[PDB]
Image 1 (cartoon, rainbow, N blue to C red):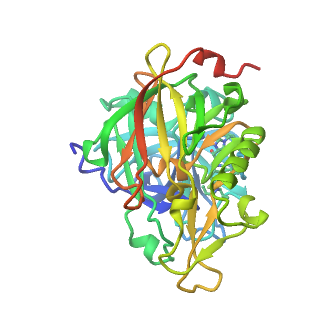
Image 2: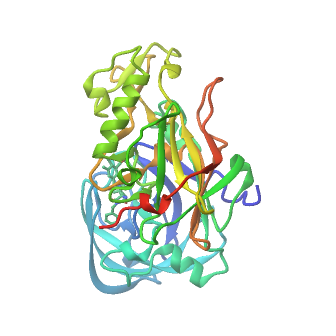
Length: 390
Ligand SMILES: CCCN(CCC)C(=O)c1cc(C)cc(C(=O)N[C@@H](Cc2cc(F)cc(F)c2)[C@H](O)[C@@H]2NCN(Cc3ccccc3)C2=O)c1
């Protein structure tokens, strides 16, 4: 590990998001910021809100610059409205650099802020093509690279605990690492495998094959990427295109048929509980996602365990049972590889080489019999045809 200053700089959990500490303004105003590879705007609460115990105060910053422009971002989940400006930004547990970046000061929001998440803003790490109001609003990471010597690359190690974290526990727990400008080798085991970033907007990738316990889901691979597949730390679940979701759930039910689970469970709405320590991990199948490799006709696979797709949740009775919600859900906007999937891997966003790397995470949750895996290579033909075109 060569980036020790950034190791363990994340806090949070899949259900409420992972955040990094940042400072905005002069003198510096400390704020916790959601790490979101699924959007491209740097936005912070800038006005009182029931769920915020602190917010960006522009009138207290000598370096604040008002852009005199409004901004609106409608996420899949929620929305916020704000005022555009720029100011000096730093990451305390990051590269020792200060940059002037665009900041959307949030003045109105609906279903955006999460009660108890402990974060006051969002860091959209994706490309300008999806930034609001338009692609002219330079994303934070672009500013960072243009203004400093920081390598055009960042890596994420999101660490799920494998068990419920209460309100005090999640505040004192290390939730992972965001390494700005590099790859830290202590965060993963085995080899890193790269998949091409298909297009620079979201971090778009191409899935070429899907297996449930080694059994081919056997769908036209173009279904797996309808209308796109993205890597998104700002989404909890593995979200799958309607048809893929239906087929995957049918296969996961078949593999786990020794136990019957209520429809509410499969809909990701209701929790299932087992007596402490008795979770039957072995009846649930591993899920393998094959990703286009950098070599022609070559792919690699990332394999996740139910310890990743079953999300730990506190029992409504706070009892001693181990409870979980099914963290795979349907999408109408393509595949979303959310935080529960990212928790099994060290993920390298290699912007400079337009590729995303995957390696088994040093902090993924597993059991004595199975482990998450990143394996390759596999001969795979016509992978370009798995990509969806409008
Ligand atoms: C991560 C905590 C839990 N959580 C959000 C609260 C339920 C989710 O798991 C979850 C579930 C669903 C269905 C969507 C999203 C959800 O939109 N998450 C967004 C961030 C986010 C995080 C958050 F905690 C609250 C938000 F209101 C938005 C992502 O950016 C998402 N990725 C692609 N995209 C499309 C897009 C990109 C750029 C501009 C417009 C649209 C998105 O909206 C998150």
